[PDB]
Amino acid sequence: EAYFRVESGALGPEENFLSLDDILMSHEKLPVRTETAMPRLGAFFNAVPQGSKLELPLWLAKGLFDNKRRILSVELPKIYQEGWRTVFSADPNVVDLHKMGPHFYGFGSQLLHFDSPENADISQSLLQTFIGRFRRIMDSSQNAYNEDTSALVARLDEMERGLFQTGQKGLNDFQCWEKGQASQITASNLVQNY
Amino acid sequence: WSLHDSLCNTSYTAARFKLWSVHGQKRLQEFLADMGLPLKQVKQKFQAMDISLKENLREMIEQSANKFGMKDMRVQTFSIHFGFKHKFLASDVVFATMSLMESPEKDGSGTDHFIQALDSLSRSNLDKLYHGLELAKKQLRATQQTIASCLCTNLVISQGPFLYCSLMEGTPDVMLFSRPASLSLLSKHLLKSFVCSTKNRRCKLLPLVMAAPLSMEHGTVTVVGIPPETDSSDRKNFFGRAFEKAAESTSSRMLHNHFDLSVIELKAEDRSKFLDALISLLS
Amino acid sequence: MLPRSPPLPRGNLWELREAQRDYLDFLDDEEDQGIYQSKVRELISDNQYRLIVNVNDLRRKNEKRANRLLNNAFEELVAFQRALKDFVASIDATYAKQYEEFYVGLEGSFGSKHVSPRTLTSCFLSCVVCVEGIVTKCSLVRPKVVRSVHYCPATKKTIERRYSDLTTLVAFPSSSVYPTKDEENNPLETEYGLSVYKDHQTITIQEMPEKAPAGQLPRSVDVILDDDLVDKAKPGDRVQVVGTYRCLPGKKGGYTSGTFRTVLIACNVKQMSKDAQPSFSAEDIAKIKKFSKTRSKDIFDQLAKSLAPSIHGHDYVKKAILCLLLGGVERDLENGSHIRGDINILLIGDPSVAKSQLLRYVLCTAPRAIPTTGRGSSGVGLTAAVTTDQETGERRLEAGAMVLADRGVVCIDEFDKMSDMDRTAIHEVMEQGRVTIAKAGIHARLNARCSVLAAANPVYGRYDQYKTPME
Amino acid sequence: MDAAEVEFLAEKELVTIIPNFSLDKIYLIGGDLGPFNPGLPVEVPLWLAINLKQRQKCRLLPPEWMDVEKLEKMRDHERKEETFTPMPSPYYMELTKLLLNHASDNIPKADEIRTLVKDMWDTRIAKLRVSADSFVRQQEAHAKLDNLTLMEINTSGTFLTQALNHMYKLRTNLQP
Amino acid sequence: ADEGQARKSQLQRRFKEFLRQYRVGTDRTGFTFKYRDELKRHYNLGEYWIEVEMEDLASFDEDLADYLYKQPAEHLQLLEEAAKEVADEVTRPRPSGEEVLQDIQVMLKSDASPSSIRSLKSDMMSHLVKIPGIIIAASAVRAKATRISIQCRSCRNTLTNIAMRPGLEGYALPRKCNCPLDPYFIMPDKCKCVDFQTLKLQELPDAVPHGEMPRHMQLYCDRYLCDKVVPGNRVTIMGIYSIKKFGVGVGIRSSYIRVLGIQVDTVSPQEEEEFRRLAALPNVYEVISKSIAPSIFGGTDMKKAIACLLFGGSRKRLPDGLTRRGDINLLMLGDPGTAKSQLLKFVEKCSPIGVYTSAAGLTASVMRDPSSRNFIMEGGAMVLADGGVVCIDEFDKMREDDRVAIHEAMEQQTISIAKAGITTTLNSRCSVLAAANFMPTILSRFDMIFIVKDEHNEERDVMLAKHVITLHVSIDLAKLKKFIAYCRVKCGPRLSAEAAEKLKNRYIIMRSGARQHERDSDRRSSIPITVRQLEAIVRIAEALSKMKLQPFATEADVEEALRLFQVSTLDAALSGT
Ligand SMILES: [Zn+2]
């Protein structure tokens, strides 16, 4: 109630520095093709050729990128390719955005700092998927009371679980006021140890 | 409860009907048949019984109990309604509270059950009352299975001026009555069944004295004393003096711990040393 | 894993007037990129009935119609197939009359319709669905009339008659009375040459084994193929049917039970598993003609080294297994003789020397390979066994293992736990190449030109290195 | 916010009680009260009427808008109109909870007032999730809520605003 | 006739005022409208069913809850038509995509004493009953036309909106078109349908009068009661005992129970921590292996090993799709002295999935069906155990064919029969815990052999006198199972670089002497090491290091596992010679 973690800026211009969600977000891998040799460090993948397909975290490919593609170029995973961008248009209420994740909107908004050609078509997928999956989170979260919700929440990602936990915290708080139950003073964080 | 499981357990029709001896269990059958109550509706819970039977139940039962020698069958009490389905008689609250405070399985100090029973008297806790009605049932079905023991085995000794009984640990559901407060009711129902059962004319007017083991480690039992039973008994007990003077004479180890005097804890070895001097003292 | 599209979306790179006038506008397709005017012509040059459509396109073109088509499939597919004949007459009216009626399949990505026979409830009635699963039977292809043509030898006229049953998209039960005297005066006579029949089958999809909750007997569903979709599925496959869902009522004696039977009137079929590799690039054939020329000295050894890297040692055995995977040349002389062109390999040795491994690799490498053991295989179940049918009750010859795997590979592991009376059933099918059966009411000769790869544990449990190779 | 503070803001509404004790004017930091003449009406803030009722020192009175007839017309007016219609008091839910729980015997026909209030509430909540779905569905940038009371706002606000922020972000991530 | 609808329009109004007005809770705390709120919260989620309770209905209006016990057929309709008029004034205005009001299947439960199947006398025909039992079968869901519409054939006259009656009763099509005699057919395009199953309920085992086979009854589930129970469940049905109307004796009918209420008899954040700390505590190993065999005592190795089989290694898919095992196999050789049957029963009881077998068989069979007169396929036990564990005793009693097939099934982990008309495959994913009493190859299909042994010294006899009363007298499983259920599904253990060079040098030196062992003595039978046994070692170390949620195994357990195996292979060494 007073532990206010630093929130995630993974949807705006640039992720926050201290947010433990973005730190684990950017760690996810991404495919690149190198433009030069990689001397003195070919141990991991001593030198590495130019024109080689490698898998690197996102944070690494932040500074190793330039406009001229001096060191390496990037190509998007298939989840954001043209293939799946039609699937997410058929009916977005069917996809398991936890397997295709578990950071869909967080990752996809950082792949816009690579000035690829099809950006005007990724920032339209996300917008049209989130709008598609809305009337199923506005209604399965404000209307699921004293139920086992661990199956209404099995196909969501970190940007959506944060909202499914705000619908419930406002349902279970009006239903606790209606029943004269939110008058008793209780232990706040000690019942967490118990 | 159902209408059947509450005739077999009220210690006022479980005495008259003698619902512990197969010879008189058919009396219950005849009583039910004289009213037109199917034996399949009487066995089902009362809230689910058909609506066409329960019209004048509380009259066709008072009537057909004259034909059997039970004329004090209607009493005067009160009842409360809260809402849509909440309907209590003032003698259901009592049997539920009295059994939340004296639950057998102990979960802490002596003042852990007291709190849970004080809780279940305010309307904001109908989940304890509605729970303390499943203990009060479990108790009442485990009392007619003890008064059925000491009357199909004749453990009521006629030790002279007063009857006498005792209990055995090996019998099931005898650790439930270990408390020195839930033992008075068992004895007071035992006397009511007995006085109706025996054929003598002397035993029908002698007070009872009962003992059941309290503590195996200290090796001690608990003892009570109840007035001579009758219909119009004045209810003026007299054992708080008898036990005192008897322990004084024998000079044994006793404890008058409670507030009422007629309940004592006694060494398992001073039983006879105490009892003989008491027999002589009451005379 | 959820198949939310017939084209695997991961690695694809490597009144009734509005509907009919909107479908036509969609089928114009010229002004944007000409995707379908490149397909109508394409099928006219191949003489096809139906064309496959992508609903993914219908969405981008017109969302309202794409939604109204996945929820009222009947009234929309009777307007699609009309405004398709209309658009084929707008190219070649001569062709547009060769065929009675056109058809239109579907494919793409339906939102919640991608269901299994276990999830196919009764909220999908009259709705395009896309069922996946295994075929576990087929029916006998039978004609079915859709039009008659009669004739009056007396009046020299010619009357027709149009038929319809409950397995149409319009569903009026017509009677097959075949009129013989329309007016009591003149007699009639049917003309079969000028009438119109069509094909008709009935298969049974069944839920995939590894998708069942394993507690029950997995659910099934009945499909009604038709009009040259007919033989497109054999027992034991993995299909993705895309067809309307329908309930067909009945009445036996003027009194109907409410219970109905629901079927799936298929209008496309897809084999999920790719079991062929003839799709090569010109860059690939370039690579191939390079590699075949680089060095003629060391290309065989270099081929065999890269055969099964997951195994150490056994270079000779890999060499020979490669020779198997290639094969010889089957010569058939002029008089009619025949000489086999296959290689049969046998591997014996102590336990745990990767024999089963080599077998399980040769299985997946070659196309059309069949596995088999030495105890789960009888002498007759390998080649061909006689049985009967349940519908007709007359005998036939079910093909054993070594006849399914024709022009293929058969992998027999623990070839030594096979009784003496069972090996003998192979001596004809391993050299002469064809099985001959003369049972009670069956006299047949099946072609079984295959190749055997077999593994056998030696006697004495381990190879006593002192006795002799023959003992 | 949270319901237990809307309930705090709602205990400032004025109601009318009938005391049965003698007391002279009191000068509260929020006004004046009294004098309390036994058997004579007086108007006080709720948080005092409730607290005096619990101590058996008064007898409440039903507010005028709390009539079983005018309410049976509000309940129909609400279902006819297609926008949020004006309501008797900005805090009617909390009034008809606190009153009817603590003074249900001084209010005639409590268990019909209660059902009509709940009928109104169950509609004004249905209009919200339609007015909060067209917003997203059409990607608006403004929405005029007409006569929403603070309680309806607070029951589904901390979700709606938090799910519109994540939409503004997704809609303005391509400009730079 | 005219008073019929006038009564109904007065019952459908008193069943509506019940849902609209019934409250709970007291006046001190605060109230709660019980059924409006559930109607709304179930409609907005898209469920369309409430669960009315009969005690409430009784306590509100006493007459209605009696009609509902006497004429349930023609009153459930009024109830379900008032639930639809209340769910309309509560959720409206529906937002955009739905504006047609659905239909609300009103279930109903109760708290009343259950009858039994043997107490269904014919005077209970069309009265709500309440019986317990056990589901024994389950049909496949089908359609059932509810609102049907017909059409003439010749003149093409329609007569639509006809409503079927519920239950198992058909409909009598007219014959007076107003055209030939019966000119009416059904229009398949216009007929609303709902699902329906058909179960089979057997009477509880402890209520058979014990001279015969238990009797059973037939049910009829509906829209939302379908696919709610699985053959093997305990239930409590509230149905309308009724008769089939599809119109041994002259006037005999069939009878079923139209179910309209069903019940079933029997993870957390804070529960996670009692798994966490227990996996983290220093002596995490022995605490389990101590509380997995209370009755039988002696030689905890035979209990050490069983601890791993409950967890198992992990399933890897190399790039080649060449998957690897994820289970283990165990053999307990030795005399049948009934000391092992106890252990089998325990491991079966405390398993997430498990079957103890001595019927159709273990593996699949091909049997000539009487009806079909043809061969059909019978998947036995090892196809029903998905990831579970199968226990076997008397490994020489099983049918010759069956033993061959179990050999192949433990070899490949799937069963593929190619016989008369059957060519299918069934993935066998289970664990074999075998007890012996034998080729060097079926023996080598396992990896761990435990034979039994004893002594007779008088201090040993003091140990025996101890063990006497340990049986003369005669960490919990209820949480052990729910611990494994979370441990198996959260750990991804592999080996660390050092375990590799440990195992290489252990295994090479295990091989290096088998030569001089078998080159001289060669007693016609022995057992050498094989790479399958090495892979068994690796998948044992995985299951050890999964006890601790430790994502990387090390030398912490490899040597003790190797010594466990030095026991398990020397056992078969002594037995086979
Ligand atoms: Zn007609």
Image (cartoon, helix red, strand yellow):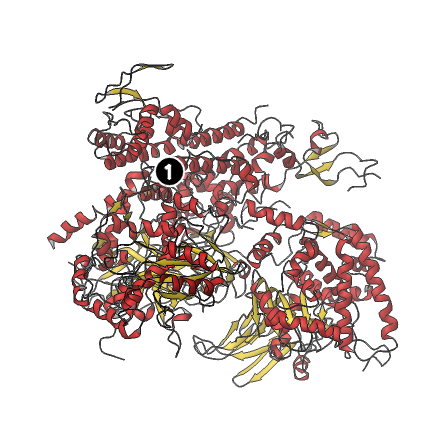
Q: Position of residue E262 (x, y in %)?
A: 37, 58
Q: Which residue type carries mark 1?
A: Lys
Give the residue at x 58% y 34%: A106
Between E306 and E36, the one nearer to me in the picture: E306
Assign a secondary structure to mark 1.
loop
The crowd level at tag 1 (other Cα within 10 Å; few <14, some 14-19, many 20+) is some
Q: Position of residue C295 (x, y in %)?
A: 84, 54
Nearest the camera: C97 or B102?
B102
Toward which corner of the image does residue A194 lie, by quadrant? top right
Is E35 situated above or below B274?
A: above
Q: How many marks overall?
A: 1
Q: What residue is pinned by disc 1?
A: A179
The quarter in which the C terminus of chain C is drawn is bottom right
Q: Is residue E44 left or right of residue E473?
A: left
The answer to whether residue A36 shows anywhere in this view is: yes
Chain name for mark 1:
A
Q: Quadrant of ligand 1?
A: bottom left
| Most foreground residue, D106 or A42 | D106
Tell me if C144 is positioned left or right of E408 in this view: left
Residue E168 in view of the camera:
no
- State the image quarter where residue E126 is shown: bottom left
- Seen as rendered, the residue at the extreme bottom is C440
Q: Relative to residue B62, is residue C412 depicted above or below? A: below
**Is C470 positioned to the left or the right of E117 in the image?**
right
